[PDB]
Structures are given as C-alpha cells and as structure tokens.
Image (cartoon, rainbow, N blue to C red):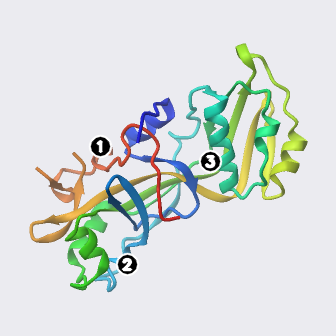
Amino acid sequence: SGLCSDPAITYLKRLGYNVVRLPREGIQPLHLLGQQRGTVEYLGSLEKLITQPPSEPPAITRDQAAAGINGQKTENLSFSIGINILKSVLAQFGAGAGIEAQYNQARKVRFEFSNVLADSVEPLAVGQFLKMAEVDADNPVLKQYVLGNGRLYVITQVIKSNEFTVAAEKSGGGSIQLDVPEIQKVVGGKLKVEASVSSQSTVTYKGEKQLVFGFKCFEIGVKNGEITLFASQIAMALDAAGGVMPSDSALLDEGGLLDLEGF
C-alpha cells in the first residue's frame, strides 16, 4: 500500500477500475483474486471454484473501444518514477532490456493512453452463475475463502492496450532529442517504436500483446443463504442495489497502484 496520486489513476478509479502496478497480458474476466493479510493473489479461472457449471457461462464481450480512457495522460512524472514504469511495461511487452540508457537526459516523462479496449462480462450474470452453482463441499476455494479467512473477488471487466505513448522533457521543460533507431534496436522486433509527427521527443511503443492495466472486480461472499456477489461500500448483494454503478466495483488498493501476486 501507500499513496500514488495521479490524474490518470483518479479517472480510472472513478470509473471503478483497479489500476495495477504492473500491466500484464494474463488478467482476464471470470478470473479470481484471493485477498489475505493485505496481499492480493491471482488465483486464475472461476472454474477453480465452480468445478461444474450450472449453466452456460457469462458471455465475454471483447475488444470494446474505451474512447473516454483514450487520450488520458498521467502527470509529468519525475524520471525516478516514470522510468520504472516504462522499464516494466516494456519488459511485459517482451522488450529487450536497456530502455533507461536511451532516456538518460530525461528529467520528466509523461504517459498517454491510446488504443484502449475493454473485455467484459455482465456482473449480474456472474452473480446468477455463482448462486446457482453446485460447488463441491470440499472445494479448496470455497473452504479457504467463502467459508474461510480469505476474501475472494471475481474480475468482470479488463482494460488493455497494445500500445502507449511517452513524452519526455529535460530540466526546465527543454525539448530532448531521442535516438529512435537505437531505442528500436534495444527493444527488438516485437515492438514498433515511432515518434509523433508533431514532437520528436514523443514516442509511441506498440507491442504484439494486449496488456491489461486495469480491471473491475466484485467481492464474493454469502448472503441470503447463497454464494453472493456484493456491491462495494449492511453488506449489499449486487443484484439488490439498483443497476450497477461505477462505485459498486471493489477497489483493492484505494491509495495507489495494486500489486498482484501469483504470477
């Protein structure tokens, strides 16, 4: 935990998204998160709990444009903060190491979102699927979370992109000349590196994978005698709240960026 305040994070959390410290390809709707003693662990597929489905599963709608998130920018980040983000995002795209050496003149870097897509299930359909399941009485997820000391959440929506844009500045805001051919040689062929038509120092990195950088989830528990999906903040079942609002999804790291274990 800790405080990481940024306009881009604030916007995404207001939409209801957890924002992860480390964007990752493997984060999916209908996957489970286990929370115990602070730490959130990525558990994997909902079928670890629902070993025999009661019905067709909630359909996943894929690749919906998120035009409100597109164009969102972070603050102008001090190098120590911004370069660790750039390094780790490029690593997750499979880039070769060494991007920091190409940005050694940068005092500040700012990120811009583009090409953001959402994959989603309908939370109320997940809630129906959960409450109608016949879970085995000895199922390990049931016993450790639903009837145990952990807290379980199910992911209902992810936001992802295969690209991002970095603007860089020198001290005082001075323009910087970046060696784009060298940057390309550093990250390798799995990335396409291109400067902006209007700014030599603004560079877009495009990979071959979609990295999830935010997700919505809802807590699983027991109410009305059944396994229940809850609105966040009496504990209220999601299907009793009146629609599903941005504020109903659970934010697991309210102050900052969410760490995920299990990868």
Which residue type carries mark 3? Asn
Determine whether, in the image, residue 68 is placed left or right of residue 193: left
Specify whether 176 is left or right of 257: right
| Vertical order, 7 against 122 (above or below) | above
Foreground pick, 72 / 110: 110
Asked if residue 70 lies left or right of residue 14, the reply is right
Q: Can you identify the residue that label 3 sits on?
A: 115
Q: What's the amino acid at mark 2?
A: Lys
- Location of residue 85 (image quadrant): top right
Secondary structure beneath label 1: helix
Closer to the chain start, of discs 3 and 1, is 3
Which image quadrant: the N terminus?
A: top left
Q: Are marks 2 and 1 in contact (CB under 8 Å)?
A: no
Are there few (<14), some (14-19), or many (20+) residues within 10 Å of tag 3?
A: some
Residue 245 drawn above or below residue 138: above
- Please name the residue shown 34% across and 84% down the image: 51
**Residue designated by label 2:** 48
Q: Which residue is found at the position 23% from the left and 69% from the top?
A: 146
- Helix or strand or loop: what does disc 3 sit on? loop
- Can residue 110 be seen at all in this image of the molecule? no
Label annotation for residue 95: none
Which residue position holds label 1? 247
Mark 2 neighbour class, 10 Å CA radius: few under 14, some 14 to 19, many 20 or more: some
Which residue occupies the foreground of this view, 236 or 263? 263
Which numbered mark, 2 or 1, is in the foreground of this view?
2
Q: Is residue 91 above or below residue 194?
A: below
- Element at label 2: helix
Q: Label 1 is placed on what type of residue?
A: Ser
- Mark 2–mark 1 distance (CA, rounded to whole Å): 28 Å
| Labels 3 and 2: the sequence-earlier one | 2
Residue 204 place in picture, x, y as percent = 73, 41
Q: Nearer the viewer, mark 3 or mark 2?
A: 2
